[PDB]
Each structure stands twice: as structure tokens, then as C-alpha cells.
Image (tube, coloured by chain):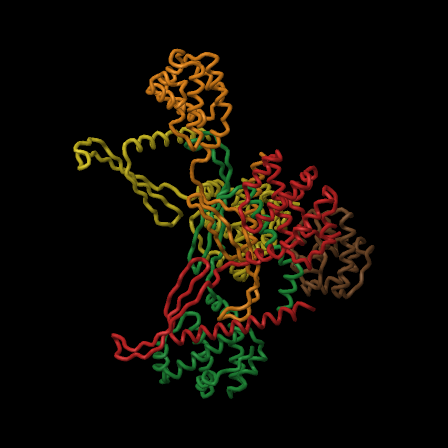
């Protein structure tokens, strides 16, 4: 019929094919392999030597291990996409042919780390730019060739933007009069007031 | 009764039709879909759609069985079937025929 | 279609027939090393030091053997054709068998190496989508303008290139409808005939 | 029991249009069909469509759906050659249910009229991905002397190339590289001839 | 919805019958609307002899105040109640308020369209084209026989009035993944619609 962990859509074909490959392993070794891939998603790091050693017993070659890791990441992320719980995912996996033992073993670790995973996914979602930092300087002009006496201030601003993780930041520089600075500050405050009522 | 369905679906699970491992559906959908995919993966001269959905009504199913009976002999089937016989779920008449298609696929 | 060898290239294969198969196997291993880890003429100095053998003719022989392997794997010609081709070199049957086996055992890796010589074209790598609705602006305060943000990743000659786009629901539906037609032709009679009669 | 050329499942655009055009007269439909055809050659004809909508008192929400339905139907119809789409099957699929009888004549006339060669010609121009060569100019020199050599006497070729993208390239090309280029071109011609021969022999069985 | 002192003084002056009658008020309001709307305006907005009896300074101050009020109301999507209440706080009558509301209603749609046309956006795609090929050989590879897909996007940048095209090459697996991604986006849109 259909399943929910894939967003209320028919389960893809590659996951169906490769979950059987996942099923030809030991549950305890799964409790460590899924932990490794989940930590990789969480940003701690992945030790491919560890997973190769863990699955070295079954002599799984490049294709099988590749598919297994892909399926683990895909299915875990898809289940966390809709905030699905362990009890429903275990039944759905049972409908997929995975033995109840493996479903229990995997959900033992999946159910106990969903919050950090989901918060990281929220933080690491699609975005175009981000303001890393800001710096400013104030100037007070005294005299000039154009005008003998001025006695008015000026504001210098710098904005640092990170366009992607592990990327150099391209700074932005500009010089502003007092009026533009004040209007910009007022408009920013208006935007914040409009934008703080959504929570 | 399932002593033979287990074997035939296990063969079709490992024959490239891993959808046969699903649970909750009648054997008809699994076996007929496996046969449908096998007839085309081998890819003889086919010029007619075999599209269907699980638990289809007869209004399309009987006609689709008519087309598969029309196309199957044209693809050099080693064994002959009868249009009324396919709805009968004659797994004895399906065990030897799928040997050719499974290995060909 | 068949390796009807060139006379000048054949002249460089005269070193091996006067050499036992024991060192011909080492020369084949050296050819594999030259493909994979690269070529280092200093290995000529090492061979001279360890065997008191001239570097020039050893270089000629290794390069000729490597060229034979490359143009034999480049066509995937059957074993019988290869046996027919090397029958003109006046080589021992054992050496002929060794050459055929060495060629056979390293075809897929070579063809994987050669595929990086074709012209480099922009290629799809990954796609990310975000959904947002515009609510306010500096001129209008209450708005509803839904749009779909897209970040498209492309690879050109080994670099990562990113594009930022935008679209609306109707255009997205049109895109899906067209791309579904794109991968529906390969299941038709014309494409099937073209892809079957060729091989 | 046939599959229509418009896809196994009819797109919503054409299906909705079937109900919409059941009340429009023939003349307004013919004008809209003319506008759609004029759009298929790349011309801008928005203003005339707006004028027609204003004249006929037609909401934009319905005119847009009608235009989309006609454009999609015609685009899918023109993909195939007339050999793969006979008029018989054409109007049989066009089957009267939710269809006028007097409009299929206009559809056939536009598809099978004197404009079909133009549509195919422009349609043929849609099958291009990379730039094509626009011009080719050269100049062969004979180096007599050089700062690093009293008498060189080395023939050389200077090449300039322009592409439809607007790119211009100028570069030198020594003799050996020129021979390599010429051999590659000849080999490509030979292989293209081989494919041309194989196409007829390996697909008419 | 804040307003400045000068606009308040202008609207205070607008109420006085001695300074403006009904006809002068209507003409000033319509002139302000024309100046805000029309793209071919001139000084002719104030060259209507019926208004040639009051000092131009007050005339133009009130003109600017009225234009500012209309702009603010359009920006904040104000309705009848807010305008009526503020005008009542300005010591108006039931005639001037009604005429102001009617004038706002007459050409509200154009003002709503105008303020929604300011700003930039990311490039907006319009359509796609695809070419299906069957790769055979390269210079250093002689037998592949693998289908490949050519794609071309048509996009227009609001920053530059042109139609640049983006081109990329995809394989069947990449095309399937791309189609799946787009279908997921469509399903997300449908989910939003259902709610």
C-alpha cells in the first residue's frame, strides 16, 4: 500500500533491495554500525575502518557495504523527517521484511538520539547566507575643502557572510551618513518586531 | 498450500523482483507482477502495455491477461497456457515456465 | 577492430621474447604500477642496479607492453582475437597465455582510468529545495507570495559549482511533468530497439 | 484499448480545457489557436491575447488554462512525425465526449497544413546543447629568423575561431598538432559513416 | 502606522471649510492620487483654476501630507475603520470622510499592485528542454553504449533584463534522483495546501 517514513509514499526500490542486504548481519554489530553512521550525521565523524572491521566477518564487498550505509542514512533521515517514532518505524520495517530482532536492535539506538539529530537537521537545513559577525566605526568630520566647517558624524560598517560550511567568508564594506544609518536601524527594529510574533 | 508459494516467491525474491518480499498482499499481485517484470526485462518484441496496479478490478485485469496471453506466445514461451487458466492460479503450470524467464532475466 | 600491430611498435616488443616469463610478469606488474601509481624513470635506475640491465630498452619494453594493454582493454576484444593478434610476435605459448591472462585480469580498472580522458561537461551532483512564503516588505506589510528555493550543484572538470534559483508551484509541476516524459522514452519501442540491436 | 499520444494519463491542463471550450464559438477559438501557433516560433504576442480577452469578456483564469491546454496538446502532437500519427487515430482519440466536431478540422489544418514544415524546421533547431562553429579563418607563416635562432625555417599556422555563443578564440597550431587534428577529424567522419550505415541495417529487422 | 507632526498639521488644516470647500478638497485628493499613480504627470496637477485662491505653500504641504497618508495606508493595508477613526480624530465631518473613503476605494487595486512591484528576487525559472543521446566512444575509449541526458534551463534575472540559460548533463540515475527531489517538493506543497 504505502508507508509513512517515506513521507506517505510508496517505499523506493533501492531501499527495499538493500534492506535485505542489511538483514544479513548481526544485531550487536548493527548497534555499532548504525551508531557510527548516526554520529557521522551528527557531525562527530566517521571511521570507515571501524565499519569495515565490524562487517569484515561477513566478507561484504564494496557494493554491499556502500548500499548498507546509504540505506541506514537514508532511512534514519527519512524517519526523522516526519518525527516518526520507534514503535511505528519498527512495524513498518517488519512489513519490509527485516526481522523483528533487527528492528528492535536498530530502534534501541534510533529512539534514544532523535532530538540531537532533529535539532542538527534544523540548524543544517538549506540556507543561502549567514551573518557571521559585524563591526563598526564612527567618524566626526571637522573641516573639508568642499565645506569649511561640517561638524557632523559618519558611520562605517562591515558585514561578514559565510556562504557555506567550510568556506571563506567574503566581507562587505560601506560608508553611511547619519540619516541612512538611523533609518536602517529603525527599519531593522520594525522588521524584528514583525518577525518576533511568530513563536 | 503455502508450502509451494513460499518457494516460488523466494525464487522471485532472488530473481531480481525483490518486491515479492512485501507482506499483507495476496499471492496474485506478487506472482503476476514478478512475471510481468520478467517478460519485459528479457525484452523480446513487445508492443503492448502491461501496466497494472495492486488489487486491480477485472475490468482491466481480464483484458490485461488477454494481452499477456497474446504476447507471451510471441516471445517464444516454451509452455502453452490458456486464458481461463491464468485466473485459476495454476502454480503447477507456472513452476516450469518461470524457469526460462527467471534465468533469462 | 582487431589489433593489427604496427611494425615500429612491434620492434619495441623484441626485448621480451629474449627474456624469460619470470621477468615478463614483473614487467606486467610494472605496467600496472605505471598506470596506477604513475611512472618514475628512476625505477630504470633501480632495475639497472638490481639486474645490471640497460635502462633504455627496459623503458622501451615496459612502454610497449603498457601501450598494448591500453589498446587491448580500450576495445574489449574477445580472447580469441587477442590470441590471434599476438601469434605474429613469435612469443612462447606460455608467455602468450601470461599476456592474455594479465590483460584479462585488469580490463575494468583500466577502462575506469580511461574514462577521465573524455571532454569534461557540467554534471549534476546534488539538489536542495526549501519552501518559503513572503509575508512583509518595506512597501507592503501583509503579503502572501509563496515560492520554492532551489540550490543546484554542478561539477565541471573536478570542481564544485553552485546555482541559486527560485520557482512557483505551477512551474515546478511543469518541470516534473516534462522530466517524467524525459525518462519515459527509454521504455518505448524505438529506444529499446536502438539499445538492443547495437549490443 | 489504445494509449493516446498525450500520455497514459491525460494531463489536467487538457482535461479541464475540454469542459471550457464547450461553449466558446469557433472564431474566438480559431484566433486563440492562431496566437498559440505564432507563439511556437518564438514571437511575442501577449498584447493581442490581452486585447482578445478584453474584447470577449473572458476571465484571465480561464483564458490561461485554455491557452495552456492547447499549447501542450499541440506540442505533444508535433513531436511525432506524420508517419507515426495518422489522422484516423488522431480524431478517434479526439473522441467527441467533451469535444466539438467543428474544431478538429482546425486542429488537423494547423497540424497538417503548410505551417508544419516551418514548425518542424524550428523544432529541429531545438535539438542543440553546445555551440556550433560560426566561421573559420587561418594564416600560414614561414618563420625565417628569430631572436633565439638566426634562421628558423619552421612553417606554422595561425587559427581563429568564432562560436554562436559569441566567443572568439585565436591561437597558434604547429604542424604535428595539425596532423593530429586532421587525422582525428577523418576518423570521426569514418565512424559517423559507420553509424549511418548501421542505423538502417540494425533497426529494419 | 505612525505619523509625523507635519502630516498632522496638514490634515488639521485640511478640515477647515474656510481653507478648503468640498470641491477644493475633492480636487486636491484626486490630484494627489494622480501624482502618486500616473507615470506621465507634470505641474498640471495643481493647474486647476478652482484652487487658485489659497497660498501655494499650504496647498503643497497638504498635498504632500495626503500623499504620505495614502502611501502609509496602502503599505499597512488599512481598511475603512482605521481611516475613519483617524480622520474623525482629525475633526472631520461625515461628508469629507465619506469622500476620502470612496476615493480610496476607487483606485485601491492600482495602489496595491504598485507597492507590491518593488524589490529584487532570485532568478526565476520558466521552462526546460532535454535531449536524449546514446554515448558510443571517446578518443581513448572505444565501446561504452550508455545513454546520457542533456538538460537546459531557461531563467530570467530580475537584475539583468535577459534570458540566460543554464545547461548541465545528467545520467539516468541522476535524472531519477532529481525527479524524486522535485516530486518531494511538490508533495510538500500539497501537504501545505491540505492543512
Colour in which the image shows chain E: orange
- In what quadrant of the picture does the N terminus of chain E appear? top left
As drawn, the chain in green is C
Q: Which residue is more in the foreground, C88 or D99?
A: D99
Q: Is residue E140 above or below residue A83?
A: below
| B58 left or right of E85 in image | right
- Which residue: 57% across, 66% down? E145
Residue E75 seen in the current view = yes
The residue nearer to you, when weighing A40 against C176, is C176
Q: Position of residue D56 (x, y in %)?
A: 62, 35
Q: x%, y% of residue A11? A: 61, 48
Q: Which quarter of the rendering shows the C terminus of chain E?
A: top right
State which chain is coloured red. Answer: D
Tell me how many marks there are.
0
Chain A: drawing colour: yellow
Residue B7, position as x, y percentages in the image: 71, 58
Say if B7 sits above or below A118 in the image: below
Relative vertical location of residue C18 with respect to residue E2 in this rendering, above or below: below
On the question of residue A113 being in view, the answer is no
Viewer-side residue, E25 vs E47 = E47
Residue sitting farthest toward the front: E49
**Chain B in the picture: what colour?**
brown
Amino acid at each position: 500500500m504505502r508507508f509513512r517514513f517515506c513521507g506517505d509514499l510508496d517505499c523506493p526500490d533501492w531501499v527495499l533491495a538493500e534492506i535485505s542486504t542489511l538483514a544479513k548481519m548481526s544485531s550487536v554489530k548493527l548497534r555499532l554500525l548504525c551508531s557510527q553512521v548516526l554520529k557521522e550525521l551528527l557531525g562527530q565523524g566517521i571511521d570507515y575502518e571501524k565499519i569495515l572491521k565490524l562487517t569484515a566477518d561477513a566478507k561484504f564487498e564494496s557494493g554491499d557495504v556502500k548500499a548498507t550505509v546509504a540505506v541506514l542514512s537514508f532511512i534514519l533521515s527519512s524517519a526523522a523527517k516526519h518525527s516518526v517514532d520507534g514503535e511505528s518505524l519498527s512495524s513498518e520495517l517488519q512489513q519490509l521484511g527485516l526481522p523483528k530482532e533487527h528492528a528492535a536492535s536498530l530502534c534501541r539506538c534510533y529512539e534514544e538520539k532523535q532530538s540531537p539529530l532533529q535539532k542538527h537537521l534544523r540548524v543544517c537545513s538549506l540556507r543561502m547566507n549567514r551573518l557571521a559577525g559585524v563591526g563598526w566605526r564612527v567618524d566626526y568630520t571637522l573641516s573639508s575643502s568642499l565645506l569649511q566647517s561640517v561638524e557632523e558624524p559618519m558611520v562605517h560598517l562591515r558585514l561578514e557572510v559565510a556562504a557555506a560550511p567550510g568556506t571563506p567568508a567574503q566581507p562587505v564594506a560601506m560608508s553611511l551618513s547619519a540619516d541612512k544609518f538611523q533609518v536602517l536601524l529603525a527599519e531593522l527594529k520594525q522588521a524584528q518586531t514583525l518577525m518576533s510574533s511568530l513563536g | 498450500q503455502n508450502v509451494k508459494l513460499t518457494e516460488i516467491l523466494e525464487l522471485l525474491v532472488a530473481a531480481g523482483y525483490f518486491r515479492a518480499r512485501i507482506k499483507g498482499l495476496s499471492p496474485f499481485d506478487k506472482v503476476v507482477g514478478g512475471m510481468t517484470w520478467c517478460i519485459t526485462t528479457c525484452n523480446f518484441d513487445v508492443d503492448v502495455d502491461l501496466l497494472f496496479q495492486e488489487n486491480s478490478t477485472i475490468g482491466q485485469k481480464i483484458a490485461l491477461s488477454e494481452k499477456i496471453v497474446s504476447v507471451l506466445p510471441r516471445m517464444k514461451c516454451p509452455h502453452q497456457l490458456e486464458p481461463h487458466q491464468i485466473q485459476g492460479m495454476d502454480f503447477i503450470h507456472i513452476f516450469p515456465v518461470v524457469q526460462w524467464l527467471v534465468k533469462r532475466a | 577492430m582487431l589489433l593489427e600491430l604496427s611494425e615500429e611498435h612491434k620492434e619495441h616488443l623484441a626485448f621480451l621474447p629474449q627474456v624469460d616469463s619470470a621477468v615478463v610478469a614483473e614487467f606486467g606488474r610494472i605496467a600496472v604500477e605505471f598506470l596506477r601509481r604513475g611512472a618514475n624513470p628512476k625505477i630504470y635506475e633501480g632495475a639497472a642496479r638490481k639486474l645490471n640491465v640497460s635502462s633504455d630498452t627496459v623503458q622501451h619494453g615496459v612502454e610497449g607492453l603498457t601501450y598494448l594493454l591500453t589498446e587491448s582493454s580500450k576495445l574489449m576484444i574477445s580472447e580469441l582475437d587477442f590470441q590471434d593478434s599476438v601469434f605474429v610476435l613469435g612469443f612462447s605459448e606460455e608467455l602468450n597465455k601470461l599476456l592474455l591472462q594479465l590483460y584479462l585480469d585488469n580490463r575494468k580498472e583500466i577502462r575506469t582510468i580511461l574514462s577521465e580522458l573524455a571532454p569534461s561537461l557540467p554534471s549534476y551532483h546534488n539538489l536542495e529545495w526549501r519552501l518559503d512564503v513572503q509575508l512583509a516588505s518595506r512597501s507592503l506589510r501583509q503579503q502572501i507570495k509563496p515560492a520554492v528555493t532551489i540550490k543546484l550543484h554542478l561539477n565541471q572538470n573536478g570542481d564544485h559549482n553552485t546555482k541559486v534559483l527560485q520557482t512557483d508551484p505551477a512551474t515546478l509541476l511543469h518541470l516534473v511533468q516534462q522530466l517524467e516524459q524525459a525518462l519515459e522514452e527509454m521504455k518505448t519501442n524505438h529506444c529499446r530497439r536502438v539499445v538492443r540491436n547495437i549490443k | 484499448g489504445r494509449v493516446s499520444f498525450l500520455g497514459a494519463q491525460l494531463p489536467p491542463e487538457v482535461a479541464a480545457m475540454a469542459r471550457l471550450l464547450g461553449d466558446l464559438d469557433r472564431s474566438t477559438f480559431r484566433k486563440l489557436l492562431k496566437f498559440v501557433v505564432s507563439s511556437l516560433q518564438g514571437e511575442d504576442c501577449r498584447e493581442a491575447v490581452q486585447r482578445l480577452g478584453v474584447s470577449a469578456n473572458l476571465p484571465e483564469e480561464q483564458l490561461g488554462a485554455l491557452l495552456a491546454g492547447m499549447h501542450t496538446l499541440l506540442q505533444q502532437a508535433l513531436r511525432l512525425p506524420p508517419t507515426s500519427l495518422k489522422p484516423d487515430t488522431f480524431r478517434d482519440q479526439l473522441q467527441e465526449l467533451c469535444i466539438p466536431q467543428d474544431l478538429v478540422g482546425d486542429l488537423a489544418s494547423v497540424v497538417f497544413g503548410s505551417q508544419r514544415p516551418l514548425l518542424d524546421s524550428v523544432a529541429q533547431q531545438q535539438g542543440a546543447w553546445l555551440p556550433h562553429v560560426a566561421d573559420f579563418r587561418w594564416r600560414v607563416d614561414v618563420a625565417i629568423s628569430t631572436s633565439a635562432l638566426a634562421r628558423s625555417l619552421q612553417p606554422s599556422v595561425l587559427m581563429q575561431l568564432k562560436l554562436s555563443d559569441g566567443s572568439a578564440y585565436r591561437f597558434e597550431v604547429p604542424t604535428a598538432k595539425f596532423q593530429e587534428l586532421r587525422y582525428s577529424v577523418a576518423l570521426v567522419l569514418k565512424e559517423m559513416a559507420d553509424l549511418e550505415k548501421r542505423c538502417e541495417r540494425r533497426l529494419q529487422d | 502606522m505612525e505619523l509625523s507632526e507635519s502630516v498632522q498639521k496638514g490634515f488639521q488644516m485640511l478640515a477647515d471649510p474656510r481653507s478648503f470647500d468640498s470641491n477644493a478638497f475633492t480636487l486636491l485628493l484626486r490630484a494627489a492620487f494622480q501624482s502618486l499613480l500616473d507615470a506621465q504627470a507634470d505641474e498640471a496637477v495643481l493647474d486647476h483654476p478652482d484652487l487658485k485662491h489659497i497660498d501655494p505653500v499650504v496647498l503643497k504641504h497638504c498635498h504632500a501630507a495626503a500623499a504620505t497618508y495614502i502611501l502609509e495606508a496602502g503599505k499597512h493595508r488599512a481598511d475603512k475603520s482605521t481611516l475613519s477613526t483617524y480622520l474623525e480624530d482629525c475633526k472631520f465631518d461625515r461628508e469629507r470622510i465619506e469622500l476620502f473613503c470612496t476615493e480610496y476605494q476607487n483606485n485601491k487595486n492600482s495602489l496595491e499592485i504598485l507597492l507590491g512591484s518593488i524589490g529584487r528576487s532570485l532568478p526565476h525559472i520558466t521552462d526546460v528542454s532535454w535531449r536524449l543521446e546514446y554515448q558510443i566512444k571517446t578518443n581513448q575509449l572505444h565501446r561504452m553504449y550508455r545513454p546520457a541526458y542533456l538538460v537546459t534551463l531557461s531563467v530570467q534575472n530580475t537584475d539583468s533584463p535577459s534570458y540566460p540559460e543554464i545547461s548541465f548533463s545528467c545520467s539516468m540515475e541522476q535524472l531519477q534522483d532529481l525527479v524524486g527531489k522535485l516530486k518531494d517538493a511538490s508533495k510538500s506543497l500539497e501537504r501545505a495546501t491540505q492543512l
